[PDB]
Image (cartoon, coloured by chain):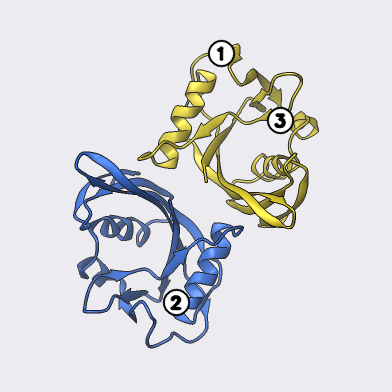
Chain colours: A yellow, B blue
């Protein structure tokens, strides 16, 4: 059971995102917690490892249980912690080993190809400073079977 | 690695706590995440099972990595998610299987016997509504070796 963090960094009405190779899906940058770290330490380190950018005061906004559901039972599960930040320092790296980095225009973000549960998270976090708690059930190919979000969309 | 939640319920300057059997340490009531739940679902079910009480709108305030440190290596690690709540419904149970429940006065809490990491947590959460992130390093007997908290006390 892994623990993943990512950050959504908004600056001049744009959002720093990463597109997976081969015209794959768009994600917020981040990565896995290392033993002994707090979630705050992880997101600053992982984010910077992946983007070259230091985020100034990231704040937690989303806590999610991610479930892979198959043949009627839970077969995998991890945790995702989504931060938000508005201030940052450093130059964006052209390429990351996970994909290409791009500032996207805020109001275009919800039209990009992304896992369905990400869309809901982005829809709350892009427009609210409230905390979001949730569960997403996916099939092994990452088709959304269902979700529980609190507060509801 | 397990995932524990608890809740600090402040009602008119009193805090609901649990004293472990043998006049041992005092804790906030709570319990471990089951597969598939969000942290918000866990704390309400666990809090209820332990106390008889329904916490109305708990909100996350503390996310901690707890580490047991022995012979110079991390030997054990778990996560604690601390919630805060003012409103609640239902009748407190006299006995629990984990120990005795009692409403204690807010300004007396820091003087109860408790693991040293919990003092820092109570010190912040009882007096602030800001998020606390941190790591506590313990010995197998729960003597605090160190901590990193943010915001720092």
* Image vertical order of residue A132 relative to residue B18, above or below: above
Q: Is residue B45 left or right of residue B92?
A: right
Nearest the eye: A81 or A33: A33
Report, in whole angstroms, how far the alpha carbon at label 1 lies from the one at label 2. Answer: 50 Å
Q: Chain of mark 2?
A: B
Residue B18 vertical position relative to residue B137 in the rendered view, above or below: below
Task: State which mark lies toward you, 3 or 2.
Answer: 2
Q: Tell me which residue sits at (74%, 34%) in the image.
A: A114
Question: Farthest right residue?
Answer: A111
| Mark 1 neighbour density, 10 Å: few (under 14) some (14–19) many (20 or more) | some
Point 24% across, 61% down: residue: B115
Q: Dividing the picture into quarters, in which one does residue A35 lie? A: top left
Lateral position of residue B7 relative to residue B140, left or right: right
Q: Looking at the image, do the residues carrying marks 3 and 1 touch, with CB atoms under 8 Å apart?
A: no
Q: Can residue B119 be seen in the rendering of this structure? A: yes
Q: Which residue is mark 2?
A: B50
Residue B14 visible, this angle? no
Q: Which residue is mark 1?
A: A93
Q: Are marks 3 and 2 on the same chain?
A: no
State the SS at label 2: helix
Residue A106's label in the rendered image is: 3
């Amino acid at each position: 059971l892994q623990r993943v963090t990512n950050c959504i960094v908004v600056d001049h009405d744009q959002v720093l995102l990463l597109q997976k190779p081969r015209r794959g899906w768009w994600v917020a940058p981040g990565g896995k917690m290392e033993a002994g770290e707090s979630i705050l330490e992880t997101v600053k380190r992982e984010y910077w490892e992946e983007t070259g950018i230091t985020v100034k005061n990231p704040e937690l906004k989303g806590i999610f249980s991610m479930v892979i559901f198959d043949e009627g039972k839970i077969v995998s599960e991890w945790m995702l912690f989504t931060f938000k930040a508005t201030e940052h320092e450093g130059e964006m790296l052209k390429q990351s080993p996970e994909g290409k980095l791009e500032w996207k225009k805020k109001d275009e973000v919800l039209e990009l190809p992304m896992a369905a549960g990400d869309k809901w998270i982005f829809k709350h976090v892009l427009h609210s400073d409230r905390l979001l708690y949730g569960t997403f059930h996916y099939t092994p190919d990452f088709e959304l079977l269902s979700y529980r979000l609190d507060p509801e969309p």
